[PDB]
Each structure stands twice: as C-alpha cells, then as structure tokens.
Amino acid sequence: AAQTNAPWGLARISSTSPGTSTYYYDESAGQGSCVYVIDTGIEASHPEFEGRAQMVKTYYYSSRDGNGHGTHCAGTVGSRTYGVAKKTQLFGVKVLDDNGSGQYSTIIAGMDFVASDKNNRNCPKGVVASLSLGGGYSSSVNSAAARLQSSGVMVAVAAGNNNADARNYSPASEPSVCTVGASDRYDRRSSFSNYGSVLDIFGPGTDILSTWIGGSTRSISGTSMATPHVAGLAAYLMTLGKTTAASACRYIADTANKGDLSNIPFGTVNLLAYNNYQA
C-alpha cells in the first residue's frame, strides 16, 4: 500500500533515503495487534481512530485526554492518516494528568496494569506498549518496565529531551526495553534528543504531524514523537509474523537504516527505524 503526501516520518520509516513523502507498507497494517499508549489519555472519538481506540484505565477524575500529548502519540501509532500501524487496536492508560505530569508510583501501577490487562484483550498478533514519558533515574520505574517487557509486551520508551546521556533517566535507562531517540527530516539527531549506549534505535521526532484533542491535528517535536513510530512499527512487524514482542527491538535494530544519521555521539547507535517493505 502507498499513502501519498504522508507525514515525513511515515515516509521516512519506509524509505532508504530522506526527502520523500509517500509511506509504503503492507496492507495488513498491524491488524490483530494491540498497542497500549501509556500517557495523558486518548481522544478515542477522533475520526482519525475509526473506532479502533479506547480508554481502558485512568488514575484521575477522567479518562479523557485534556492535554493532547497522548492523543498525538496514539495518532502516530495507529491513526488512519498519521499512524504507522493503521489497523492496530489502541488502548489508552492515563497515568499522566492534563498538565502532562504523573507520579512514578502511578506510572509503575500503569505498567503493571498493562501486563495484566493484555489478558483481557484480543491481540492474536501481539502486544506493544508505548511510553512517551520519563524522569530521573529510578530503579523501581526501570523494574516495572522490565516486568512489562518480560510479561510478553514490546515496550518502547522515549530516550528523553535533555540532549544528555539517557543512562540518567527512567524508564529510558532500562536495558531490556526499547529506548528510542529522535531524528529530523534531514537525518540529523534532533537537537533535544538524549543519546548514549542505552539507546536502541532512532525514529522521526522533529516536526511530527499527528492527531490532537478537539478533533484537530498539530505538529510537535520530541522523543515522545519518535517512540510511537517504533511502537507502531513493532505492531506492524508482529502482525506480519516477522518478529515477536520479546525480539522486536533487536529485529528493528537488525533491519534499521545504518550509519545515515548525523550528529550521533561516538558510542550511540546510528540506527534509524525502517520497515523494509518492498512494494
């Protein structure tokens, strides 16, 4: 399948070169997979989600996304126009309030929630979790992400936006999950992207168009935007049967575009997520 005039990041993940604008992907499109977006919520009524998104858990007075961040990330995972995996099922877990903040204890509870809740859902092709959040190093936060991964969920986490080594941030620094840095449309490391040996992969993160609350759209930047590209890619590849939740991060690294990004610090992987789809 070909989506013309796609957001640059979608085109990038199906291309061996920057500077194109058509996204190419297998029509299976993540059908039969599920992606949990652990964030500020999802505006599931947005026409872009086509009834495939639902809120399953909140720790606050509403499950609605009063911020937009979670809706944007969910759109990059799986919206019809802005998403990588256009037929996946999206499940929202609201661990962040409408200001985008959340206590680590709430975030940990949300990760343990997903590890159990997947047993209440139909995801024959596999389960992914996208975590566009983080703070300073916490062994308890890292352990929760490790448990979620161990339970059979492909965990993708943001590296962080400090232009610093991600070893000092959580869950970015957990070795067993997939830690995602951000790049721009010219294949440069995004100015804010964290780096370091704990990164596994880069995805598009600067000037990413996606869904927003109020049935709208907007372009924003962050490792929060790169992460759902990788989460959606994992769901897509799992639906194709090419990899599993336990092996998808390594597979994405195996099949990435290699050595194409600029301003990658010595010791950080130079790997850009790529779906290797041959039309």
Image (spheres, helix red, strand yellow):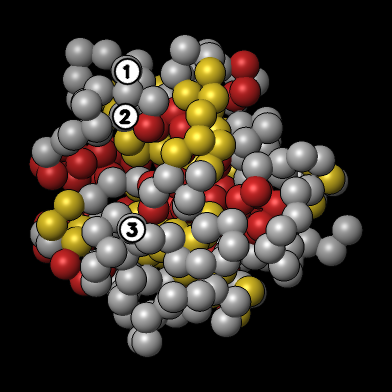
Rounded to the nearest angstrom, the CA distance separating label 3 from label 2 is 21 Å
Frontmost of labels 3 and 1 is 3
Is 216 or 231 nearer to us in this picture?
216
Q: Which residue is mark 2?
A: 40
Q: Are marks 3 and 2 in contact (CB under 8 Å)?
A: no
User: Which amino acid type is marked by label 1?
Assistant: Gly
Say what secondary structure mark 1 lies in: loop
Q: Give the quadrant of residue 14.
A: bottom right
Give the quadrant of the C terminus. bottom right
User: Which amino acid type is marked by label 3?
Assistant: Phe
Say what secondary structure mark 2 lies in: loop
Crowding at dot 2, Cα within 10 Å, few <14 / some 14-19 / many 20+, comes out as: many
Residue 66 — which label?
1
Q: Are marks 1 and 2 in contact (CB under 8 Å)?
A: yes
Q: Give the quadrant of residue 95.
A: top left
Residue 29 horizontal side relative to residue 234, left or right: right
Q: Can residue 246 be seen by looking at this rendering?
A: no
Residue 192 — which label?
3
Q: Position of residue 31 (x, y in %)?
A: 68, 40
- Earlier residue among tags 1 and 2: 2
